[PDB]
Length: 49
Length: 49
Image 1: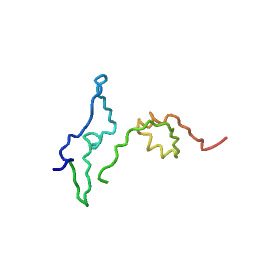
Image 2: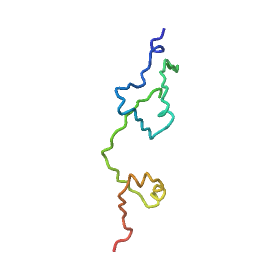
Image 3: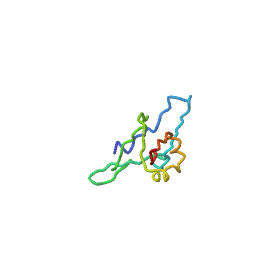
Image 4: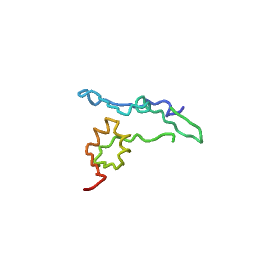
């Protein structure tokens, strides 16, 4: 059982609500909009979770 | 690289003094963002009295 593959990945948290989350993203490239999926290298093997 | 670093935005305290031949700016003044950022045109007279 891989501990990394079964863990809730924190994206954000709201300590607020006034003001609401205002995300100005002027560099709206796909990695900067939808997020990145980075990988770990294990002996030349690409892995992700 | 498998995974980079998420570098946060940095408030810029420097000021940029570009230097260029006028035809080098003829191809760079087309952006309205250029006019908004660089506002002081220090233009050298090619001929002195």
